[PDB]
Image (cartoon, rainbow over the protein chains, first blue to last red):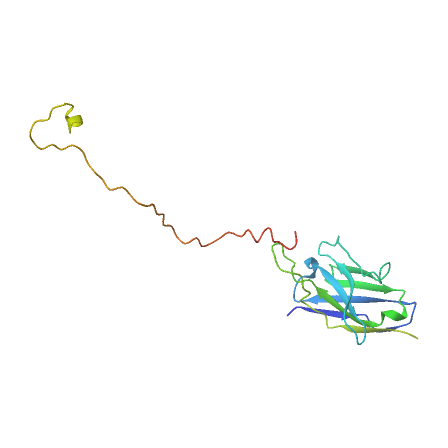
Length: 125
Length: 49
């Protein structure tokens, strides 16, 4: 129904940079709080960053803090994440997921319902 | 009977003095079974303001 497709990842050298793009289809991405989940190869998932619907509340992961910027292209109706100065420990798959309870009278706990397909990034020589 | 005729001496006869009426022994109220409530635990329990 509603998909969250990724694009821009793959292999890179350490020190270099990269940009991940999150494309929303099936609904309007300009008013749904988003946040990224990274999953290294053969491990669980891990939080990356977070954009709000407002655009004024942003919470990053403590390790990618200071770099690895996130944003949304409300013109192109995407989410953008530019990975800058990567190191060897960032190899993982990345998912772009949207928070379910985005109404004003929800009375329901949080849950990332629309999940991303996920694409891999590999950082080495 | 003396008090109703307002006279200390009553002559022979039959007199209608007063009335009696069984009192109610209980009080009951019957209303419809309270049903279509309003959404309050929907405004205080909101997850995001």
